[PDB]
Amino acid sequence: KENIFLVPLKHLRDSQFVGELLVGTPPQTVYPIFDTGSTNVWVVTTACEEESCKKVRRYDPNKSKTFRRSFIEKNLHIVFGSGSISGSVGTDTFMLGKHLVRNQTFGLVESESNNIFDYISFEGIVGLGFPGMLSAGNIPFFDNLLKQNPNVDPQFSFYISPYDGKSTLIIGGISKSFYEGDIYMLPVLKESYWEVKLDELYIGKERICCDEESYVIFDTGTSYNTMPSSQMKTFLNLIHSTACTEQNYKDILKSYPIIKYVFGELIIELHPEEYMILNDDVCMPAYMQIDVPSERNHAYLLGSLSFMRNFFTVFVRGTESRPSMVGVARAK
Ligand SMILES: C[C@H]1C[C@@H](N2C(=N)N[C@](C)(c3cccc(Nc4cnc(C5CC5)nc4)c3Cl)CC2=O)CCO1
Image (cartoon, rainbow, N blue to C red; front, side, top):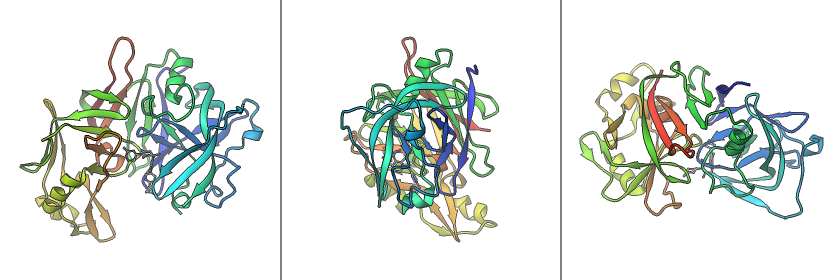
């Protein structure tokens, strides 16, 4: 009975962090993406006979004594970048870091449509968002874990470290060996994504955003950072792709601007060596244009590669005594 426990995260060859999850009895091992930009739990099953599903640990429900199916024909389909996932719904017992989660609803990947799944070794998703993005089931996975493990405090934090393979997901609390200084908490505006109000956004000395209401989403399943299309045009007029090598990377980016996010009295800065990534012989901005249609108010994503590699993020679920908050600190 470990009230504070650690689930080690392994950065795969691509742009996602996966951890160990046991599904069923006797347990079957899968390595799903731990996602805070969605809520549903997906697991890749043996009913999927495509090569994209092969060469990856597949979960067989016919070998689980605790797997139960229902007669309601609730079929799930979610878009997943270039591909899409389609499957049925069921319930089984899960185990995440020596903690049992019984009678949990999850999606069973039965068809993988398009080569993205073959590249990333897709084995499932474990959503950690708020209820309301749950497509099927009565209770989300993380909510059910806290219910069946009352001693665990309703919070988890991500320590992202892809360079050395020491990334980890800590559930139930925080450790000073993953961050330095003090954590600044931000209130969560709307309980769909892990969303936070954004007051101002500065590219160098120029104010580019927050004429209208804008928000920040902390998505551990999105590698890059994002801005709306309107601000992304201004972003690239000031920030350009340049040729660089591993030896001259620091001197070339010495002239580049500092990106400042304003959260009330808190200011978060992304230095050029922190938001510029080296691919082949060019340094490119780790930023994307995604227009989030969930809320007409356009929002900004803080991802795993650029933001979380340098900042320790804390996801505090609200209870009857505290509201839901996101806390950020400098990574150690
Ligand atoms: C408002 C947010 C919601 C986000 N969002 C998720 N966070 N979850 C889902 C399941 C998701 C969709 C697509 C990709 C990924 N993840 C992933 C990343 N990168 C690579 C490497 C190959 C390039 N493969 C996979 C994921 Cl997790 C659904 C989804 O829309 C997307 C950005 O807007």
